[PDB]
Amino acid sequence: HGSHMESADLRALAKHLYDSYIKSFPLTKAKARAILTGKTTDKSPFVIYDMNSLMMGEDKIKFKHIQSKEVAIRIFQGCQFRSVEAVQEITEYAKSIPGFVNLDLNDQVTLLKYGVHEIIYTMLASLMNKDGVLISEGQGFMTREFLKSLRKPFGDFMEPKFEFAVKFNALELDDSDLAIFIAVIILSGDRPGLLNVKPIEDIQDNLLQALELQLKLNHPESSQLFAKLLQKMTDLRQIVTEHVQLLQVIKKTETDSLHPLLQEIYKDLY
Ligand SMILES: Cc1c(C)n(Cc2ccc(C(C)(C)C(=O)O)cc2)c2ccc(C(=O)N[C@H](C)c3cccc(C4CC4)c3)cc12
Image 1: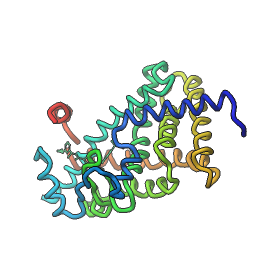
Image 2: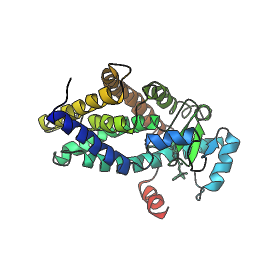
Image 3: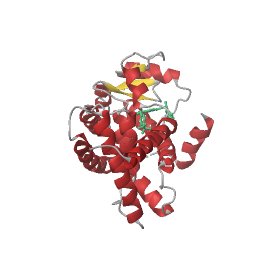
Image 4: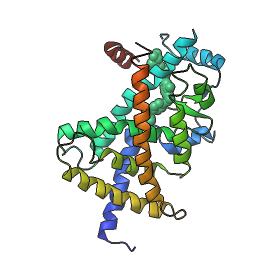
């Protein structure tokens, strides 16, 4: 429909959330895609396609701590070290969402608990194509087929992430669309264990309308793209369930997981 004063607010909200999306996250989908196509002035990332290429990229790494079994551990421990840094960047973006910090602190924890994994899955699509995924803030690129070649419990922990990304990146969403799409996931008013739901649903419905207005403007072709995104929010919860069910098996009937003190030692040291 036509414009008005309310449309001026949703476009300003979309820009405000976009400004926070650029600052909260260092590698946006715009630059992440520019690295994959080689059309960026930055150096080409190191490619990990076989076991031999992996034993050359680790020589560029500073540390050296964990045999064909230590590979599946170091690789898994790697994204675990980015997942902990992910929450740092996701929380800063969540705090920048207008009205999130005014919620109850117990709800802010509950929204971030069940929602951070879906954002990790969502933003992971911005870093990967049909061949591999960008790792270490665009410094490396690990092949999808190489992640399949890992040991049996670890050859299937990245594949659900690639299958969702191929269907998700087929929508050609940009940083402006993904900015509003993440906030809607954060402000999911039906997270198990919320205190005040009404103030959260007001923000989500406000973010939903700012998202639908964004998609109608930023995507003239392909109607019902807003309905396609809402189905992806339902797909993520099914994928996170299969991921958290697989993560508890590798952390209890496989690895030791990383020690709590060692993780903070590696964070502040390098
Ligand atoms: C498997 C893997 C993925 C898939 N990546 C991409 C990735 C991007 C972005 C995200 C988030 C969630 C932040 C996102 O933006 O969506 C997640 C995963 C990686 C990024 C870096 C590394 C990694 O080993 N680094 C260094 C070398 C490192 C740092 C500390 C400790 C160690 C080893 C214990 C000694 C290694 C691994 C991976």
